[PDB]
Length: 93
Ligand SMILES: [Zn+2]
Image 1 (spheres, helix red, strand yellow):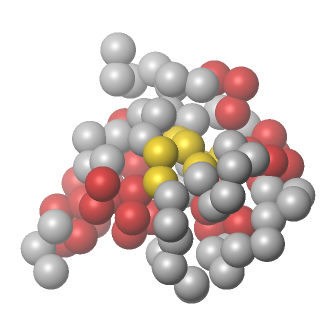
Image 2 (cartoon, helix red, strand yellow):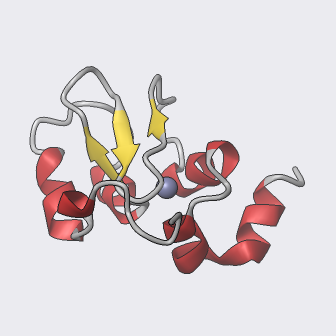
């Protein structure tokens, strides 16, 4: 299902934040890991443990939850943590 994570090995926040040990980019690693992302080890590429959606080319001080909702609104981890109202608002500008 979409209710199960694509990468269960990254389902723990502690595991995700660990992948950002070598993170030099201007996007907050705690916010990234909170939003479900872990680092792939190539540039600023990250992937969501649940939906598998990848993001790259981050702008400085960008909001990871906003980008998660912008590009991958069907993610069930995004839904659980942020709710449908938030996802809809992101797409209403
Ligand atoms: Zn996701």
